[PDB]
Image (tube, grey):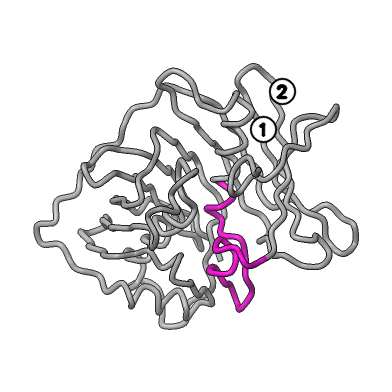
Amino acid sequence: EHLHPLLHRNVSDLRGLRYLSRFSGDESVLAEHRVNGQAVLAGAAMIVMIQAALTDALGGAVPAGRGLVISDLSWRQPFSVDAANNGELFLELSMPAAGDYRIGIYAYDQAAQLQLHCQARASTAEVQAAWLDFSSLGAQVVDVEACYQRFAAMGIEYGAGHRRLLSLVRQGDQALARIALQDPALNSGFALHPALLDAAMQGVMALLLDELEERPALLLPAGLGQCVLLADCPASLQVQIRRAPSTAPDYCFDLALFDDQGQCCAILNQLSFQP
């Protein structure tokens, strides 16, 4: 059986720990995430793959009230399934020093050249919750369809399984989003479902509708300072989003994911979007 819906097989050998997933292109993380008309693996899915790989390498579970921390992640080229790569996406995991893990996600092109798609470092730590800080007094209700229309105008179209933004409210440079899976049962087997993590990232558009023009340039996640996984995430979530300073021509945000009761389940610090 697959080790994880997004981490199919363990192919470790003397070169080191390594994992392999083969996608057909019909999977929701690809087919329901189309960029300029092509089914492309959502950046969130690679974060989930790192989390699954680390959890497996640690014996199948994170230990002792600690959190899985992914740091200094960068997305390079988008991944699409084609005849060249046969849908095969590899993840290499090394530990150059105790508790200091290095990850690379890559695939092969038509030229037999290895292409690096994602790179990050990981660790485990005791971590402290973010606090749901959002006061809606005076808040603005953001039209979710206006957000998806803006994404569509830049070239990003989502299928129903990844159109999980249910509501948005904006208060200054902060926004609060409600997201939930189309089929809650599909949360089975995921500590954090990629569609919910992707929907959390979609929420940043609440803060950009006024800044961006009708036909803005395509913006995609390019870097992430930290992704902290504190606890299993339910099928319904609240997402607090705060605009952060960024150098041009980029945009940066901090996000925190909470359950319907306000418990912090995951934190994303310094999520950078770039043309």
Which of marks 1 and 2 precedes in the sequence? 2
Residue, far front: 1
Which label number is shown at residue 119? none
Q: Is residue 132 left or right of residue 212?
A: left
Would residue 170 be counted in the magenta stretch? no
Q: Residue at x 20, y 44 (%)?
A: 133
Image quadrant where one finds the C terminus: bottom right
The answer to whether mark 2 and mark 1 are in CB contact below 8 A is yes
Which amino acid does the dot numbered 1 rest on?
A: Arg
Secondary structure category for the residue under label 1? strand
Image quadrant where one finds the N terminus: top right
Secondary structure category for the residue under label 2? strand
Could you say which is closer to the camera, residue 110 or residue 232? 232
Q: Residue 58's spot in the image, x, y percent?
A: 60, 24
Q: Is residue 81 left or right of residue 27?
A: right
The residue carrying mark 2 is: 96
Q: Residues within 10 Å of mark 2 (few under 14, many from 20)?
A: few
The residue carrying mark 1 is: 102
Q: Residue 200's spot in the image, x, y percent?
A: 39, 55
Q: CA distance from mark 2 to mark 1?
A: 8 Å
Could you say which is closer to the camera, residue 171 or residue 231? 231
Q: Is residue 188 left or right of residue 263?
A: right
Would residue 35 be counted in the magenta stretch? yes
Q: Residue at x 40, y 79 (%)?
A: 149
In the image, the segment drawn in magenta is 25-47
Q: Residue 161's spot in the image, x, y percent?
A: 45, 66
The quarter holding residue 261 reads: top left
Q: Is residue 49 left or right of residue 141?
A: right
Q: Residue at x 44, y 18 (%)?
A: 64
Residue, far right: 111
Which amino acid does the dot numbered 2 rest on?
A: Pro
Q: Residue 232's spot in the image, x, y percent?
A: 40, 38
